[PDB]
Amino acid sequence: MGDASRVRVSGQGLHEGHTFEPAEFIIDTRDAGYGGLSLSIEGPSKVDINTEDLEDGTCRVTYCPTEPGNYIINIKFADQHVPGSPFSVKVTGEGRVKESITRRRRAPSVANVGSHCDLIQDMTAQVTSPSGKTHEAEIYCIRFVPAEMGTHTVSVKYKGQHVPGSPFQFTVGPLGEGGAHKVRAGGPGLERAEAGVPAEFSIWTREAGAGGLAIAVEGPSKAEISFEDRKDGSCGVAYVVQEPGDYEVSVKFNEEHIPDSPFVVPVASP
Ligand SMILES: [Br-]
């Protein structure tokens, strides 16, 4: 003597929410006759819920999600799911844990001193200063003395072809920004992971001088992470995450997202 299909549910909170912001929907039971309402909201965490019997025999439901991601709202009437139920809700916001490692090189001065080496002998090496002046460099180990501050470009060629790692950049002085677009990344840790199993990827910033590279994993639990600078100038990153869920791995170079960052990374259980 009730009819679940006559139950109507509407409102933004049926499809969309935001972290620490109330999401709301109306349950209209007026045409459903006799029967009880049961309601649950399942997702990354349990969600506080409020209801208000409105004047017009309607019931306003208000919920507050504390963690982003994919939720579902179960609405049953007389132990039967109503039309549209369960409703998929996507909740945007900051993951609850953000785990980052951020690698920086600073070199705040220029000084006409070639007492160092910051950078099979038929090799041509050229350097282009920030002001665009290109000049040939002596030669492993390139001897060029920057006179200018800013991002330099450095190309090393054998037979007139670039070697491994060339062309690259060499920034001296105060960092500010820029260069994120030319940064590269790849590895399975950038599209999926398994809880408790290391997930790797590599980064090539092509920056031989000053720069800042921030790798972050944001999502429902803690991460263990490791980072290695490699001989070739690349970066290895590995992370182990504690719980299954939807995570975000972001690579920022001098404060800007590299081209596919942040990468959505579903993490499965063991
Ligand atoms: Br990799």
Image: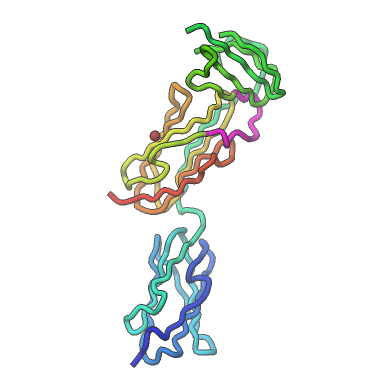
Residue that extends furthest to the right in the rendered view of this protein: 131
Residue located at (43% from left, 67% from top): 88
Q: Is residue 243 left or right of residue 120?
A: left
Q: Position of residue 69 (x, y in %)?
A: 45, 59
Query: Tell me, what colour scheme is on the image?
Result: rainbow
- Camera-nearest residue between 107 and 258: 258
Report the number of discs.
Answer: 0
> As displayed, is residue 216 above or below residue 231?
below
Q: Is residue 172 magenta?
A: yes
Residue located at (47% from left, 33% from top): 203
Residue that extends furthest to the top in the rendered view of this protein: 121
> As displayed, is residue 93 above or below residue 193?
below
Residue located at (68% from left, 24% from top): 130
Image quadrant of residue 84?
A: bottom left
Q: Is residue 157 magenta?
A: no
Q: Position of residue 61 (x, y in %)?
A: 48, 77
- Camera-nearest residue between 224 and 5: 5
Q: Quadrant of ligand 1?
A: top left
- Camera-nearest residue between 161 and 242: 161
Q: Is residue 90 left or right of residue 139?
A: left
Image quadrant of residue 229?
A: top left
Q: Position of residue 195 (x, y in %)?
A: 32, 47
Q: Position of residue 123 (x, y in %)?
A: 53, 10
Residue located at (51% from left, 58% from top): 92
Q: Which residues are magenta?
A: 170-183
Residue that extends furthest to the left in the rendered view of this protein: 270
For the N terminus, the image quarter is bottom left
Q: Is residue 53 left or right of residue 43?
A: right
> As displayed, is residue 77 above or below residue 183?
below
- Camera-nearest residue between 130 and 217: 130
